[PDB]
Length: 51
DNA sequence: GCGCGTACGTGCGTTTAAGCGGTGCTAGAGCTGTCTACGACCAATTGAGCGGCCTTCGGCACCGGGATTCTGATGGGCGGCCGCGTAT
Image (cartoon, rainbow, N blue to C red; front, side):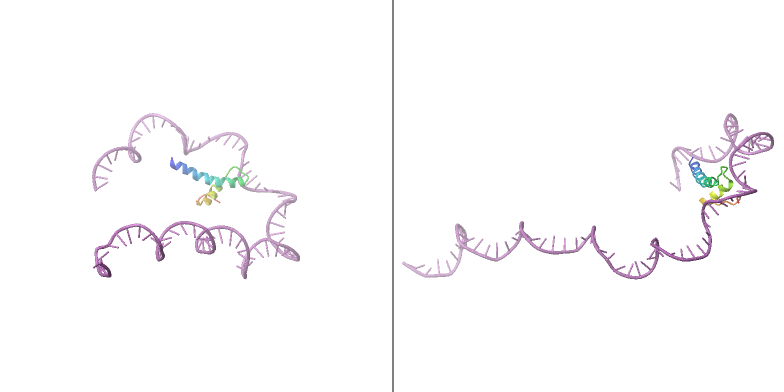
């Protein structure tokens, strides 16, 4: 139960960062691309899927 | 170290819902195409900003003068010294 709470914490913040750009971009269908930059912000850079 | 307790791992059976590949639909990203507003650039004038330089009143904490309270030598008067001393 404890971890689910955190998992949620983490998703929330990242998706929070991600969603804004997508809105910024005048679109709904939020991209994988945002998922990542948003991750790069919080400080969890990912190698694999992007740009 | 040791001992008590119990909770969490390992199993089977029951059960529940992910993953698969099948189709359909249209939304929303991506492209594309024309206009023009807003930002860069160059100019000239102006005062906000920085170095240089020294300001004044208020607040913390040390202070100031005057009446008043407590301690000390002074002193006549009632008593006691019993022991040397003059007079008959």
